[PDB]
Image (tube, rainbow, N blue to C red; front, side):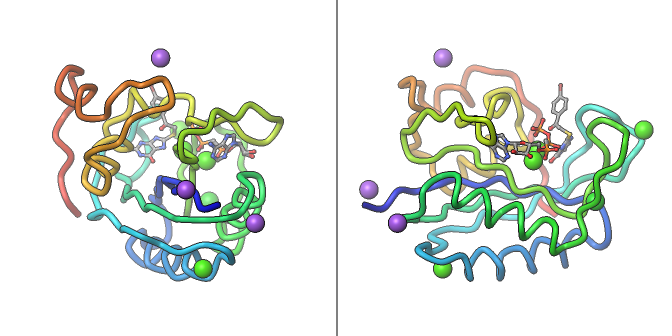
Length: 160
Ligand SMILES: Nc1ncnc2c1ncn2[C@@H]1O[C@H](COP(=O)(O)CP(=O)(O)OP(=O)(O)O)[C@@H](O)[C@H]1O
Ligand SMILES: Nc1nc2[nH]c(SCC(=O)c3ccc(Br)cc3)nc2c(=O)[nH]1
Ligand SMILES: [Ca+2]
Ligand SMILES: [Ca+2]
Ligand SMILES: [Ca+2]
Ligand SMILES: [Ca+2]
Ligand SMILES: [Cl-]
Ligand code: NA
Ligand code: NA
Ligand code: NA
């Protein structure tokens, strides 16, 4: 059985365009998986701490037969192989961030994975690229992406 995973991409260090292109190549090389769709790249102001560069944000649809945690292993590996370093400050800048937003209709609460991503419904930098690639999306709780984006106040997201 194949499931579409929706993965958010963020980068604000060490040439984000290069980082995101390298990540797309690496995502392609994940086994049991195929990239179905790539969003536009967006240049977004930082949420959380603001004393950092703007982000390049994007979303990808990845159809896979991997187990969710097995997909997470690959995304974490790719981040680490692209130089991601853990420092003290909460929500610091990073070379690459790969968040599993959704894994089909699944609701996952394990030590390493919480899906849907806990805060995606409150982040334009996640929802707008997701709507670009999956305008018909429905969340596990039945909420429609189109309805969220019609109703909630979010700034326009600007393309890179
Ligand atoms: N849906 C998900 N996608 C990716 N990692 C997830 C996840 N659910 C839980 N995690 C866990 O998240 C842990 C911490 O990841 P971090 O990348 O440091 C959070 P962040 O992306 O900087 O901020 P955010 O979670 O507010 O977006 C990972 O080690 C991983 O086990
Ligand atoms: N634009 C942009 N800003 C970012 N800030 C972070 S840190 C976690 C985070 O999303 C965050 C979001 C909302 C609140 Br409230 C606090 C933290 N990552 C990104 C990113 O990918 N893009
Ligand atoms: Ca593949
Ligand atoms: Ca700071
Ligand atoms: Ca994140
Ligand atoms: Ca993350
Ligand atoms: Cl980093
Ligand atoms: Na399926
Ligand atoms: Na499998
Ligand atoms: Na809900």
